[PDB]
Image (cartoon, coloured by chain):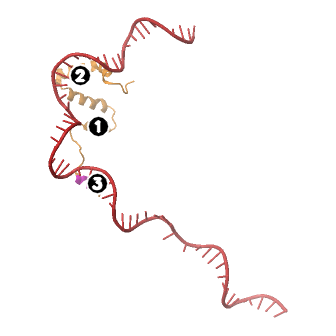
Chain colours: A orange, B red
DNA sequence: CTGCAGGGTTTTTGTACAGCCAGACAGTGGAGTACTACCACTGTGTAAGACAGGCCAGATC
């Protein structure tokens, strides 16, 4: 039941998946694992995501937050 | 049918080579950090009813 096992079982559960992903990256996008695996979530979730899919996906390195400028906080408070 | 027992199945759980990045450690000098205490003072308490005395007005002989 895929809830809490460690790395070295999912390893061979998805060896073929990651080999195919690397093959596709080498064929079409050069082989950048990060850019492929970050975008994999977009369409797989977006078939049926509520709205939080987009938030947690844009929660990437960009943005970012550290928090709002103190002026915006002051405006919220007053 | 039950019970246990060699081994199978596939799957885990971990140790194994071996190279290498990410963040903690020490420190510093002090800053600005961030979190606490101290200080007087607030709000929600919120209306009729019982009893004693004085007196007056209407009924009676």
Query: What's the residue at 27%, 36% (across, down)?
Result: A57
Please state the horizontal and vertical placement of residue A25, each as a whole percent of the image. Answer: 19, 23
Between B53 and A49, the residue placed more toward the observer is: B53
The dominant secondary structure in magenta is: helix
Q: Residue sitting at 31 percent across and 31 percent down? A: A45
What chain letter is assigned to the residue under label 1?
A
Residue A61 shows up from this direction: no
- Secondary structure under the numbered disc 2 in the rendered image: helix
Label of residue A21 in the image: 2
Mark 3 sits on what residue?
A: A76
Q: Is residue A55 magenta?
A: no
Disc nearer the start of the sequence (1/2): 2
How far, Cα to Cα, is label 2 from label 3?
46 Å
Mark earlier in primary sequence (1, 3): 1
Q: Is residue A71 magenta?
A: yes
- Crowding near pointer 2: few (<14 within 10 Å), some, many (20+)? some
Highlighted magenta segment, given as a residue range:
A70-76
The number of numbered discs placed on residues in the rendered structure image is 3
What quarter of the picture does the C terminus of chain A occupy? bottom left
Q: Tell me which corner region of the image, top left, top right, bottom left or bottom right, holds residue B43.
A: bottom left
Left or right: A25 as drawn, with respect to A45? left
Residue at 25% x, 21% y: name it. A18
Q: Which of the two discs, 2 and 3, labels the residue nearer the N terminus?
A: 2
Q: Which residue is mark 1?
A: A56
């Amino acid at each position: 039941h895929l809830l809490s096992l460690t790395r070295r079982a999912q390893k061979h559960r998805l060896r073929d998946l990651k080999n195919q992903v690397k093959t596709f990256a080498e064929k079409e996008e050069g082989g950048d694992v990060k850019s492929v695996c970050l975008t994999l979530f977009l369409l797989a979730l977006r078939a049926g995501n509520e709205h939080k899919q987009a938030d947690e996906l844009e929660a990437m390195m960009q943005g970012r937050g550290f928090g709002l400028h103190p002026a915006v906080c002051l405006a919220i408070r007053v």
